[PDB]
Length: 525
Ligand SMILES: O=c1ccn([C@@H]2O[C@H](COP(=O)(O)OP(=O)(O)O)[C@@H](O)[C@H]2O)c(=O)[nH]1
Ligand SMILES: O=c1ccn([C@@H]2O[C@H](COP(=O)(O)OP(=O)(O)O)[C@@H](O)[C@H]2O)c(=O)[nH]1
Ligand SMILES: [Cl-]
Ligand SMILES: [Cl-]
Ligand SMILES: [Cl-]
Ligand SMILES: [Mn+2]
Ligand SMILES: [Mn+2]
Ligand code: NA
Image (cartoon, rainbow, N blue to C red):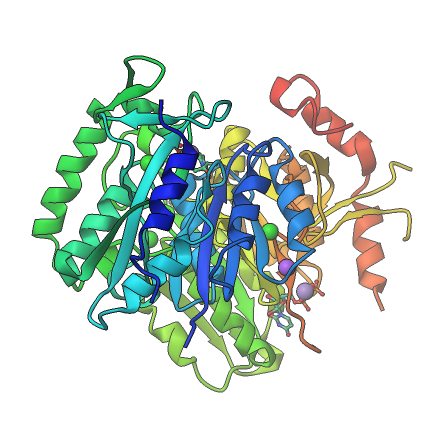
């Protein structure tokens, strides 16, 4: 046998779903699919339903998948592209695309697949037929990419799937987001909707409108058993069935108002206990402390940053410099924030407030991942997972950052790796911009904030701390505009003084630390 042409004929034979046009968002995830992704995108641009946007989230592809999607996204306003800077799984990438999407209806399409040119039209009409309907799905077929023949799944040409789901945007803010596993969470989220809304509000359009490419070592190969060249058996694996039993029980036992909070996004800890095979989340085995200073001139920026990072950490330390009162959204955090209000500009140490909590944590011998942020930077949804995972790459023995400065060894002769600019490979540097750094507290045995004498140059004093402790500063790899600026219309005598007094710099300062450790060996070229 059977072919894709036979499916196309059956669809034209049917009128199901052919009788105000809201924006439809299609969320595409991609991971090393450069051979397939342009076919996936073109099958959406050729959709009958014309009021669409295609949201593409690349999950840190090592091939040129994102280069292709970036090329296409600049040809049209219907395509927008984003890149996670670490491999976190398709469901983390879907949730990132949802937050970027703008449509009232949300569909999905994996990058290794294509679909029928009438899929969104027919499914949208079925969805909106009955105003009490919450979501719609259609059927899919597995295909051999060479021959365009149907691979039968349990001896059927087509069957209902989960990638074919379409739903109103309100689902995600009422019951939360996809669980950030590697596989299975579409089965979970489907049955999460059915619990909350009632399965009768899930309409099924039983037509073969989605065409799944069959490729080896993909995510669903976990469940495959080959019979012949035209049939396979789909049967859950052990690790998949542990998860199915798990969320079924969870669906019964979890108060339905809590789904919204159990499955928030972004996140850094597993929502459900799963083996490491099922999760790519950082899962820090120590607490995560986010430290930020802010001024009232940038309250619109600070509101954004607290919303994104609120679930990306265990605790905040907020230093308000000149606020009239604590904004609503900061004290809403409650105990998650240790706020420090400073109303007199004369009693202010300014950006040195990023390191107030560092003294207390060392004095109490409490460990954690210490992150410092500014209030003019837009942090992506994968920020804290990426930083902890890069820190773990060097076994927590180093400090990582994004705004890196490298000096001559004997401005204008500094090389500046700006945080919003790209960097292809990790590169050791001399100074990291403290709006973007991260490190483990147990690198440091002693610390006193009194050492940070003058304000306005916290970046420099922190390098001197790292140098005097034999600690290396790593500028990690990143796509362009992973972080971005939101200055929005918002010498150096002491600067040059502190540098020369504490020489040497350049690669002479870095090479002693790269010297005999093989994980650092490629940081210095
Ligand atoms: O770490 C990963 C693994 C997979 N995928 C994407 O998830 C989608 C579905 O994965 P796969 O094709 O492996 O699923 P299957 O075809 O086995 O059902 C594809 O677009 C992959 O690029 C992803 O974004 N990140
Ligand atoms: O009086 C001030 C001015 C600035 N900052 C903080 O200093 C950091 C960086 O400020 P800015 O973006 O001006 O620094 P630059 O990027 O120019 O180094 C942010 O946390 C600001 O809220 C502060 O606490 N008090
Ligand atoms: Cl990006
Ligand atoms: Cl899956
Ligand atoms: Cl948390
Ligand atoms: Mn696939
Ligand atoms: Mn700044
Ligand atoms: Na675009």
